Image (cartoon, rainbow, N blue to C red; front, side, top):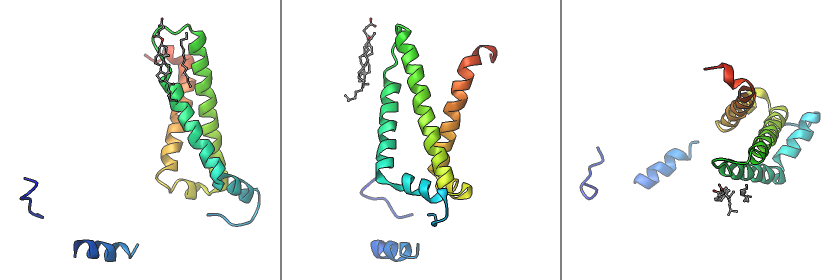
Length: 128
Ligand SMILES: CC(C)CCC[C@@H](C)[C@H]1CC[C@H]2[C@@H]3CC=C4C[C@@H](OC(=O)CCC(=O)O)CC[C@]4(C)[C@H]3CC[C@]12C
């Protein structure tokens, strides 16, 4: 089926067809933008992503509840720093600019989802 599969040049046509195809210096806007575009900041945030998945991997059954409290506090810290970086990118870019990346919208959804998870865990008993 692989050998005989009909289509119903190629590279050249694709190249020809695909050949068709920030922020200024005003205020604290520029300060935040200069901070958040620095590759150190992105390396830091991917390191925090790595540490957060490390925290997600450390759950296990019948934890001493001193370990569970540590995991909950670490989740608080990580979601707080993710919210901080999301707000920093908001105040560096524009709102319309931030919401037009297709990744920062995903990050925004996950940050608010984790925040809502944190708030619900306090009063999750009454939902049912
Ligand atoms: C730098 C690279 C290696 C990434 C490392 C990721 C770790 C955060 C992951 C790797 C496998 C996980 C561990 C796999 C084995 C368990 C045993 C579990 O304890 C037990 O089941 C026995 C004790 C008991 O229950 O009575 C506690 C969590 C723990 C250490 C896990 C904690 C998180 C770990 C270390």
